[PDB]
Image (cartoon, rainbow, N blue to C red):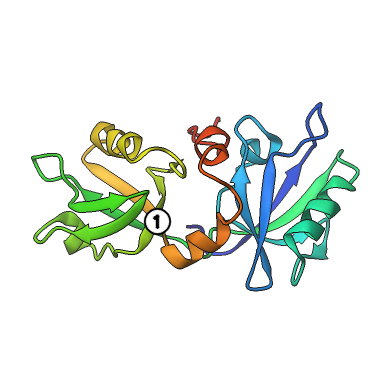
């Protein structure tokens, strides 16, 4: 999680699309969905990023509908956004034990227990936290089995980005786990 604000400049694609769904949370505006192969993924927008401004207008107090409307009426050539990096999330670095375990159980992406004497215990991994990202890869909406696969295939050093479950549940409200699995960008970013 970067320690502050950044400018991103977007162009609408062929189809007039940027590849975002935004959600009003606590009078801010947050990234709910980043579509694979979109302008939003190419410029590096992430699930949970806060949108401070759009074209130098403050988003504070906007409905999810008004943010979507402002974006639909922007001269798509150049759209500026001021972004605060994933403010609800934290990153935890863990090390697999020789059995390949970091040391937790999770269900529907939510950590439910920490195994005694594990890297997860030593590193203060918390329960009631949704997994947002593993080693920089968005995993939101993947089956638990695909998440376990990713942790299997990772090197010994595992980075996990988590979010308090109450906040996670507030953001993904009104995005059933088809688009979440289907259309949430799960790729490694392009260079």
Left or right of residue 172: residue 140: left
Place residue 134 in its image quadrant: top left
**Residue reaching furthest to the top:** 14
Crowdedness near tag 1: few (<14), some (14–19) or many (≥20) residues, C-alpha within 10 Å:
many
Q: Quadrant of the C terminus?
A: top right
Specify whether residue 84 is in view: yes
Tally the marks: 1
Q: Is 58 above or below relative to 32?
A: below
Left or right of residue 186: residue 51: right
Q: Is 56 above or below relative to 178?
A: below
Residue visible at 83% across and 56% down? Answer: 55
Left or right of residue 123: residue 79: right
The percent coordinates of residue 181 (x first, y second) are 49, 37
Left or right of residue 86: residue 72: right
Residue visible at 43% across and 42% down? Answer: 139
The percent coordinates of residue 82 (x first, y second) are 71, 58
Residue visible at 24% across and 66% down? Answer: 124
The residue singled out by tag 1 in the image is: 130
Between residues 84 and 140, which one lies in front from this camera angle?
140
Q: Is 2 above or below relative to 133?
A: below
The percent coordinates of residue 27 (x first, y second) are 68, 72
Q: Tag 1, which secondary structure?
A: strand
Specify whether residue 45 is in view: no
The percent coordinates of residue 144 (x first, y second) are 33, 41
């Amino acid at each position: 999680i970067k320690q502050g604000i950044r400018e991103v400049i977007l162009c609408k694609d062929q189809d007039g699309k940027i590849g975002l769904r935004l959600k009003s949370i606590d009078n801010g505006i947050f990234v709910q969905l980043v579509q694979a192969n979109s302008p939003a993924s190419l410029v590096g927008l992430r699930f949970g990023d806060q949108v401070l401004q759009i074209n130098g207008e403050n988003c504070a107090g906007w409905s999810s509908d008004k943010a979507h409307k402002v974006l639909k009426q922007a001269f798509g050539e150049k759209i500026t956004m001021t972004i605060r990096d994933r403010p609800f999330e934290r990153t935890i670095t863990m090390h697999k034990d020789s059995t390949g375990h970091v040391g937790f159980i999770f269900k529907n992406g939510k950590i439910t227990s920490i195994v005694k004497d594990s890297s997860a215990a030593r590193n203060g991994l918390l329960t009631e936290h949704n997994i947002c990202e593993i080693n920089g890869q968005n995993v939101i909406g993947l089956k638990d089995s695909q998440i376990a696969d990713i942790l299997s295939t990772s090197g010994t050093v595992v980075t996990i980005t988590i979010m308090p479950a109450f906040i996670f549940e507030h953001i993904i409200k009104r995005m059933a786990p088809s688009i979440m699995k289907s259309l949430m960008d799960h790729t490694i970013p392009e260079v």
